Image (tube, rainbow over all chains, first blue to last red):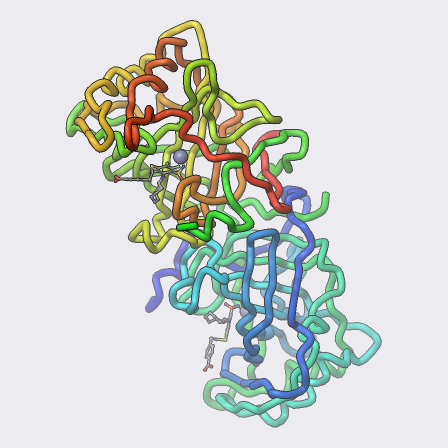
Length: 241
Length: 241
Ligand SMILES: NS(=O)(=O)c1c(F)c(F)c(SCCc2ccc(C(=O)O)cc2)c(F)c1NC1CCCCCCC1
Ligand SMILES: NS(=O)(=O)c1c(F)c(F)c(SCCc2ccc(C(=O)O)cc2)c(F)c1NC1CCCCCCC1
Ligand SMILES: [Zn+2]
Ligand SMILES: [Zn+2]
C-alpha cells in the first residue's frame, strides 16, 4: 500500500515465453569493463534481511549497446528453499533454483534517486542459477561467508573478485524488456536483461544459499522472490531468433 | 568551438540505409492523442533565425511504447533553397526537399533542462516533405503566415490546427535510433523516430518555405540543416520487415 509504484501496469518480474519474444537484431552482445577486480580494496557483503547484497566499487562499466552506458552499483540474489525453486523470472512457467541481479545506473545520472522511474535510468543483468556437478569457485567466495552474516542486518568484508565470473559466459543470447524494481518502491523504467545461458552452482552451494541466512523476527531468509507480474502488452525482445 | 558536445560520438542527423535497419516487431504503432487542436487559443509562430518554430500547448500526448510517454513542446522545420533540398536525415544518400520535427518531452521529466543529455528525455518525430502535384492544406496554414515573420526574431499568432495532419499516413512504419539535437548544445540521448512515408507539398509551397524567411546579418534563412553524422555502431531499428 505505502508505495503506489508497486501497483503500476509495467512491473517485474515476468514469465518469459520465448515463442512470443520479438527477435531484434539491434541487440548486440553485452560489454563489461572493469569487472575483474583486484583483491583490495575489499567489498561489503550484507544480509539486508530481504537478500544478500554485494556493494560494488566505482569503475565497473557496462554497455547494453553503442551509447547505452551504465555503471554497476550492486549485486544480490533471489532464492527458494529445500526442494522449492526461487528465481524471480520464469521461463514458460518454469521457476529456476535461484537468480542473480547486477544493478546498474545510467552514466546520465549521478544518483539512484534521480534515475528512479526515468526511462533506462536503471538496468539490471539477470541470470538464473541452476544445479551443476562442480563447486562454482567464484560463487564460493561469497557463499563461504554467509555463515558470518546469518543474522539480519549483518555484513562482512570480502576480497575483490572477478564479478563477471558470477554471470554466464554467453553475453550474446538474452531477453530484454522494460519493467520495474521487484522491491519497494517498484519504480518503473528499469531495463531488464535476462541471459539465455544459466550459471551452475553445486547442490551444496544452493543449500548454503537457501539455508544459512535469517531475516525479520526468527524467520529463515528463503523464498525471497516476488510473484510473476503480467506483461500487460509489453513485448519481450530476444537477441536471437 | 562553443559546444564540445557537437563532437560527441552519437550525433544526429544520420543517413538511413533501410537494408541495414534492424526489424523489431516490438516497435508498435505510434500513438498521438490530443493533436487535433481547436481554432482558439492561438499558437505562437516565431522566426528564431535558425528555423520557424510553432509552440504547442499542453495535452498533446505521444507514446513510443507501453509506458513510454511524451508531451509535445514545439515543432519546427529544416529546408533548402531554390533547386536544393534541405532535409536533415537522408535515405541512402538522398536528401528530401524539407523535414518537419515535432519535439517532445518525456512525462518522467518536469523540465527540458533535466531531460537534456538523459536517454529518452527528448523524443523527436521526423517526417520528410517532398514535392507533389497538390497544395497541402495542413502546411498552408503555416506557410501562408511566414511573410508576417520574415524578419529574424519576429513572431505572430496563428489559429490552432490539427498538428497530426502535418504527418504521414501510416503510424506503424518508421525508423528509430538514439542521437542528438542537430543544433547546439547537441545534447545526446534524443530518441529520433523517422517516418518511412513522406508528406507532399506543392512546388510553390516549398519555394514559400525556403524563400520567405531572413536570418542573421542580411542572410536568407536557407539550408538550415546539419551535415550527416556517423552511426558509430548504432543500429537503426525499423518497425516493419
Ligand atoms: N530485484 S531488485 O533489484 O529490485 C532488488 C530487490 F528485489 C530486493 F529485494 C533488494 S533487497 C531489499 C531492499 C533493500 C533493503 C535494505 C537494504 C539495506 O539495509 O542495506 C538495501 C536494500 C534489493 F536490494 C534490490 N535491488 C536494489 C534496489 C534498491 C533501489 C535501487 C538500487 C539498488 C538495487
Ligand atoms: N533539430 S533540433 O530539434 O535539434 C532543433 C534545431 F535543429 C533547431 F535549429 C532549433 S532552432 C535553434 C535553437 C533556438 C534558438 C533560439 C530560440 C529562441 O530564441 O526562441 C529557440 C531555439 C530548435 F529549436 C530545435 N529543437 C530544440 C533544440 C534547442 C532547445 C532545446 C530542446 C528543444 C528542441
Ligand atoms: Zn533483485
Ligand atoms: Zn530540428
